[PDB]
Image (cartoon, rainbow, N blue to C red):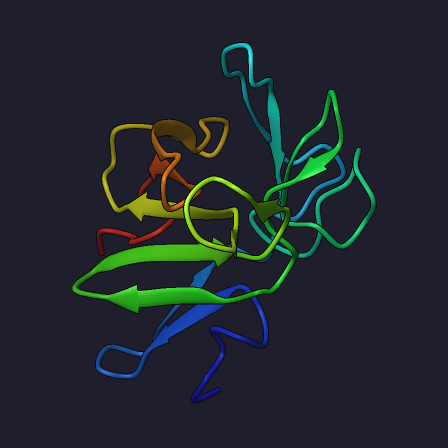
Length: 142
């Protein structure tokens, strides 16, 4: 119950006893981000991403190129949720680093669960994709 961020896709706020559930957001298709010539990405907000070799967390599903392995590692800080899938494909752009996908869950009641983390920016130098999902699921206004 103390540390959940690496265990299950849930966050416990011990100051108000509020559990956040992002674990029910597991799926076969997951959430999809339609993106340019690079392609459309599949994203598992929890678990592992399918339509690509199961065990990735973010992958272009049309080419099955991994851009983050499924490591259930979410981040709860300053009332803004985040989850990261790193070390998918090796990036030969700048340094010998991998491509990683970071999803920033902006706690905003401006969308519902059908909405999804879109790609707002992609730093091709650090080989990092920045997704953002404005969702009240991330922080529930109680």
